[PDB]
Image 1: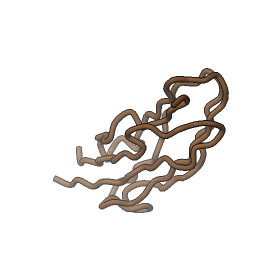
Image 2 (image 1 turned 45 degrees about the vertical axis):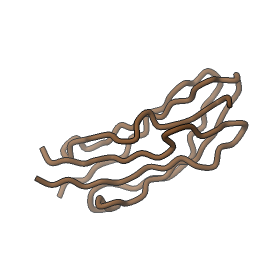
Image 3 (image 1 turned 120 degrees about the vertical axis):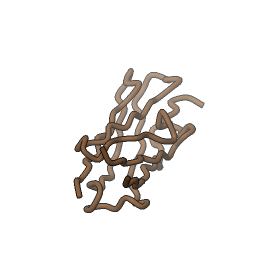
Image 4 (image 1 turned 180 degrees about the vertical axis):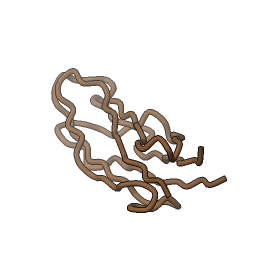
Length: 109
């Protein structure tokens, strides 16, 4: 498989006070062209519009591009809550690698 797109890790941990989660997405074994995947947040115990700002869209990798950073905004209100991000719908010859979903763990300062 070429143009393999994944999250770098199955979990990332952030502080609620950071205002943003910075989530790396990599593309490996480049064939030389563009690739696209879709991405979307999904609630866990962290909930959209309470704990974080939901987002969905497309990640278009131009030729040569090996990674992206997703930035999901965090909201302020011992406490731990999780949301998820999922990759789907590979286009232009792209494939999903492992992990293609990830969990963002929001912790109190």
